[PDB]
Amino acid sequence: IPSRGAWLEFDVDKRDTVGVRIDRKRRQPVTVLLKALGWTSEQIVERFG
DNA sequence: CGAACCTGGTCTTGACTCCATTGCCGGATTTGTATTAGACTGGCAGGGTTGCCCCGAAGCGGGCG
């Protein structure tokens, strides 16, 4: 929660996945956001092995 | 018993004053409408965190002509 910004939440749902809901609208997985910052899949496995 | 009175109003008549009420009539003001020729070309921007309940909508896994 910031001050006067936009929220973002990283949950773990009923399954073994991880919605990354960004600004109140219909969830997400992490990898869309990690690649959206510019992390390759190898960098994802490297950071999260 | 009558004469004369003077006074209760009762009402009218005429003369005079005042005053509203239109009626023009002109100036003040008030409201509407139109017109300005260099070019100018897709909005800010904010909030929002309760909880529970009922119901209806969109979707995903499941089978099938």
Image (spheres, rainbow, N blue to C red):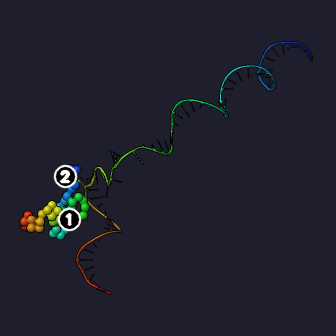
In the rendered structure, the answer to whether residue A17 lies left or right of residue B11 reads: left
- Label 1: how many residues lie within 10 Å, few (<14), some (14-19) or many (20+)? some
Horizontal and vertical percent for residue B56?
35, 68
Image quarter (top left, top right, bottom left or bottom right) of the C terminus of chain A? bottom left
Quadrant of the rendered structure where residue B25 is? top right
Compared with B62, A39 (above or below) is above
Residue A49 is marked as none
Horizontal side of A2 relative to B4 (left or right) equals: left
Residue A11 shows in the view: no
Q: CA distance from mark 2 to mark 1?
A: 20 Å
Name the residue type under label 2. Answer: Pro
Camera-side residue: B9 or A19?
A19
Secondary structure under the numbered disc 1 in the rendered image: loop
Residue drawn at x 18%, y 70% as measured from the top left: A15
N-terminal of the pair, mark 2 or mark 1, is 2
Determine whether, in the image, residue B9 is placed left or right of residue A45: right
Residue at left offset 25%, top offset 61%: A25
For label 2, the residue is A2
Instruction: Tell me residue B53's x, y (percent).
Output: 31, 64
Residue at 22 percent across and 50 percent down: it is: A4
Foreground residue among B26 and B52: B26
Residue A9 shows in the view: yes
Q: Position of residue B11 (x, y in %)?
A: 80, 26
* Residue B30 x %, y %: 51, 36
User: Can you tell which mark lies on residue A28?
Assistant: 1
Chain ID at mark 2: A
